[PDB]
Image (cartoon, rainbow over all chains, first blue to last red):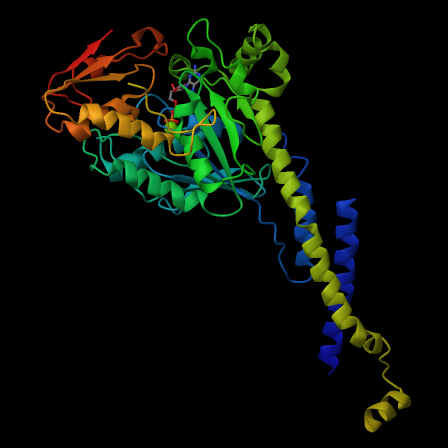
Length: 27
Length: 331
Length: 98
Ligand SMILES: Nc1nc2c(ncn2[C@@H]2O[C@H](COP(=O)(O)OP(=O)(O)O)[C@@H](O)[C@H]2O)c(=O)[nH]1
Ligand SMILES: [Mg+2]
């Protein structure tokens, strides 16, 4: 359960970062 | 030499690739492949190597493009070339690449006007290129010569179909100027695989060999045979110029002088020439890469919404929370 | 006869190529008829349509005579000696340049 929690949080932050990069790339 | 229209797009690909690699996933950067269809001795190899910006293909009178060479450009950190059939060797000189291509063709087809459906896979790594597929197909003919089989026409056409009926491919249709456009096979093929012109780009070569007193002014204006993207005229090196080792800079200067002096083409001077074709293809690739962004956004947005409902609780996890324990117990 | 074409223009129907061949076949498939196959010099001989038709209707070359009509417009640095000497695509009666 701890491993699943940690993976979910890492993936959440990484997805947010990906959107923050793509939006800036599109301009 | 060189191609400077890649420089403004490479960092966009790198940033998108890094953005996706952050999650352990790739980017669906499905750039179109470029296929050069043309008749024999139409000039379809000199155009291609002028787009790459390197003098590495065999070219010249006769049947030279005997096998369907496939060139893969891969973005890397240094510049080198390799062949799948020469695995383990490294090529640091394009002249060696050209000579090796000739040797590999002769080794399989022989010294007559032979062909082979099996492609050569040449890969060039360089920090100044994009991940591109370039296909140099053998030119179509009408009758067999040498030791070719009677069906040489059909075998060549079949080699073309497998590469131009594929989606996401640019058909760069090359026809000579000192001929009648109504009798160009490349355009017949394009109309058989792209009935409405969305990808097909017309290129007209050999404008310097027109019969004195005649021009193609009514062709370049897209009046004789309307094509959705028009026709781009170019002037390549002549056979004497290949044998004379003419510089690329001189060829471009001669092309620019040709268009500026020719009485029937001055008004189109800024719509033709090698660098114009480079911009048109680069703009076509840029339009493609932008068109796919809505799909990437929708995938990421869907994944984010799916996980958020559980992230809301995971972010509130604490090593000591009697309420969390109680909630789990009740549920 | 009208020349052969691949791409229709000018409101010609899509099958213009087949109609042109149908006109051609009614004169070149007759016996007791000579066929003179006209090919340009500036366009590679392997692409010649006249030789394809002559080859289809005169496999033996008894009636076909070849002519190369545009030696004036050859790209500088090349020539057609290998065609006029009947070496590249041997034809029983040879080729005549004009
Ligand atoms: N002057 C001139 N020569 C050309 C042009 N296009 C092709 N050539 C020459 O035609 C010969 C054969 O061209 P190439 O590209 O090898 O034909 P392909 O490779 O079979 O498509 C070479 O000597 C070229 O320099 C042109 O537009 N102008
Ligand atoms: Mg060619």
